[PDB]
């Protein structure tokens, strides 16, 4: 449960969380509201788990791409920056934080690939891709090469492939059209053909990967590479006299790198939405706020126009923002993993000679569509070991009806399958979260687990307590007791499901007195409220 009257902020470990804490300190001094900054490990996978519960931090800082799933799961609150505030930030940054037409985060920082070049080899680096062949010929005669960059990962070759017309998902009217992917079009083929031709003419090696390119550039053996701000410190350390500039154009058009936008989102379950809004809009997203975070750890380019003008005195920061404005926001939808796989396969196959460019992109298109269809199926349906020519959505399979007859467990149908319920009286000694001695001797929970094991379907364990007559507030001791009881039951189920053909997900959640089943004004009613729910999700009914 989130603590009203204060703010808990999650930001990743590689950011300037100490400077974020300073901004929190000034927030406290000015308003008395204390701000706590944390960097939990894997916070991007923690947040969707705890916020679904209603727990978590009030503010989460992460790259914008994951916020799409959170927004889909309803974990983020819509934000309401006014017109004057939105004009303070670069317009394109607001597109990175829109889900179904609703603003759902504040853009902080901006990141994209750039052209990195050796100033001693190349004081005036080429403006166009097309002029790189002749440049490599000249540099080959010196014992050098023009350009080496990671050809294994489509993140790095996509800027050229998109330049003349390739795209991932058509972005029209603030939404991504997963039916309109632009891998198999002429622009994509023209770019991928140019890339393949550089390899056939020996200007590049098809095996070149991230490590090979970095070593060659940082050793002064190639005049240019393509990388992100995360690579600059290794170049600094190699002391190669280097610069950072706009990516070359292709057929007169900008290379279009994908843009990652560090964003700040507000938890939908937060009871401090007004405090969060005020911290972000009036303290963090300001020259002073951003500068404080940036001194701790560089943000790179930033969405806030006024501070970006200050950071852009470094020509490398200016180039990052320039490439980002010419690029495309990374789509925040799950179908991107079909796009990435399909394109990755296409490029290594065209570059290796295994396929022509047109066959490889033709296959990428049909592969991606098939992949997206199959991913949806595993979301919306269950692929299960089925009896051949009993419907467990209408008839509980044996031995469940027997277990339900033993006087301790009940069931009712649920919109997502079956809700099993058992009162916690008797399952646990008074005030106890360890399972009663009686339940252990009878193997109540483990036989229930063994009864579910031959069948698919995830489980959700939810503990509830009664509450005291006429109190409209929640008891925090009752909350933790229900959470501990739920965890005991879920662990015991997991253990007894070890022999299942399924590795189902089993979550546990304490609801305390928040979700009563009946009236707490009588013991008749309080009894009903002291219970454990097991939601068995075998499909929608």
Image (cartoon, helix red, strand yellow):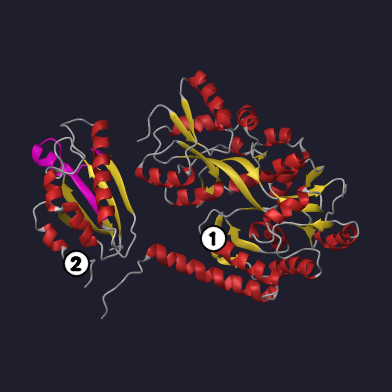
Question: Which image quadrant for residue 253?
Answer: bottom right
- Which residue is at the front of the view, 301 or 494? 494
Q: Is residue 385 above or below residue 253?
A: below
Left or right of 199 in this view: 407: left
Residue 476: image location, x then y, percent? 27, 31
Left or right of 383 in this view: 363: right
> Which residue corresponds to mark 2?
397
Question: Which image quadrant for residue 526?
Answer: top left
For label 1, the SS is helix
- Which residue is at the front of the view, 497 or 403? 497
Q: Is residue 531 magenta?
A: yes
Which of the image's four quarters has the N terminus?
A: top left
Residue 438: image location, x then y, percent? 11, 46
What span is in magenta?
A: 512-535
> Which residue corresponds to mark 1?
337
Q: Is residue 529 above or below residue 414?
A: above
């Amino acid at each position: 449960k989130i603590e009203e009257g204060k703010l808990v902020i999650w930001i990743n470990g590689d950011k300037g969380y100490n400077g974020l804490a300073e901004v929190g300190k000034k927030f406290e001094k000015d308003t008395g509201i204390k701000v706590t900054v944390e960097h939990p490990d894997k916070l991007e996978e923690k947040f969707p788990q705890v916020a679904a519960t209603g727990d978590g931090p009030d503010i989460i800082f992460w790259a914008h791409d994951r916020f799409g799933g959170y927004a889909q799961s309803g974990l983020l609150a819509e934000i309401t920056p006014d017109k004057a505030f939105q004009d303070k930030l670069y317009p394109f940054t607001w597109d990175a934080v829109r889900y179904n037409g609703k603003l759902i985060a504040y853009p902080i920082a901006v990141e994209a690939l750039s052209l990195i070049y050796n100033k001693d080899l190349l004081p005036n680096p080429p403006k166009t891709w097309e002029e790189i062949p002749a440049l490599d010929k000249e540099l080959k005669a010196k014992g050098k090469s023009a350009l080496m960059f990671n050809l294994q990962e489509p993140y790095f070759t996509w800027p050229l492939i998109a330049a003349d017309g390739g795209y991932a998902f058509k972005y029209e009217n603030g939404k991504y059209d997963i039916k309109d992917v632009g891998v198999d079009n002429a622009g994509a083929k023209a770019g991928l053909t140019f890339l393949v031709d550089l390899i056939k003419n020996k200007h590049m090696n098809a095996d070149t990967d991230y490590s090979i390119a970095e070593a060659a550039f940082n050793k002064g053996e190639t005049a240019m590479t393509i990388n992100g701000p995360w690579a600059w410190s290794n170049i600094d350390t190699s002391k190669v006299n280097y610069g950072v500039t706009v990516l070359p154009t292709f057929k007169g058009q900008p290379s279009k790198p994908f843009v990652g936008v560090l964003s700040a989102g507000i938890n939908a379950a937060s009871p401090n939405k007004e405090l969060a809004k005020e911290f972000l809009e009036n303290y963090l997203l300001t020259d002073e706020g951003l500068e404080a975070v940036n001194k701790d750890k560089p943000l790179g380019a930033v969405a806030l126009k006024s501070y970006e003008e200050e950071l852009a005195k470094d020509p490398r920061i200016a180039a990052t923002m320039e490439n980002a404005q010419k690029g495309e926001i990374m789509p925040n939808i799950p179908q991107m993993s079909a796009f990435w796989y399909a394109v990755r396969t296409a490029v290594i196959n065209a570059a290796s000679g295994r396929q022509t460019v047109d066959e490889a992109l033709k296959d990428a298109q049909t592969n991606a569509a098939a992949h997206m269809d199959q991913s949806r199926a595993l979301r919306n349906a269950i692929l299960a070991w089925t009896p051949p020519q009993i419907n467990i959505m209408e008839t509980l399979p044996q031995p469940l009806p027997q277990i339900l007859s033993e006087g301790w467990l009940e069931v009712r149908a649920d919109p997502r399958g079956w809700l099993l319920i058992f009162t916690s009286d008797g399952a646990f000694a008074t005030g106890q979260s360890k399972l009663s001695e009686e339940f252990k001797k009878k193997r109540n929970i483990e036989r229930l687990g063994e009864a579910l094991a031959p069948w698919p379907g995830d489980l959700e364990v939810i503990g509830h307590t009664d509450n005291k007559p006429y109190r409209n507030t929640s008891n925090n001791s009752n909350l933790k007791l229900s959470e501990a009881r739920a965890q005991t039951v879920a662990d015991k189920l997991r253990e007894s499901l070890a022999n299942s053909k399924y590795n189902r997900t089993v979550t546990s959640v304490g609801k305390g007195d928040q979700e009563p089943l009946d009236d707490n004004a009588t013991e008749e009613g309080r009894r009903r409220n002291r219970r454990v729910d097991i939601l068995w999700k075998i499909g929608e009914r």
